Length: 35
DNA sequence: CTTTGTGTTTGGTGTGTTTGGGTGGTGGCCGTTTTCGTTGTTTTTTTCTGTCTCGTGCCTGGAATCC
Image (cartoon, rainbow, N blue to C red):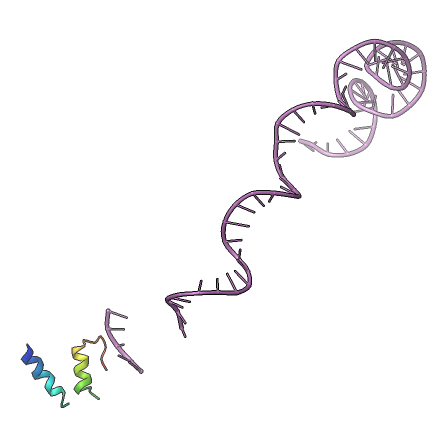
């Protein structure tokens, strides 16, 4: 679990469809409406 | 067939008169109503008792989203 969390979070440090950090934020903070 | 005009008859009421009686102004007898003295009273004025009110010692007083 820690390994998976790090393997997912580390690539986020290097990054009209919403993509990248705002889209990952929508996904993890499960939103009732999206951009 | 049957309505009104009255023919005739009878009851209600407008006047007049005599009579009488239910009842109207005075009188004088009596216990009623009224006024004075007595008793309770209550509430308004005066009084007896503690918050306000103004001077001290000290020592605290001051940029979106989701739930």
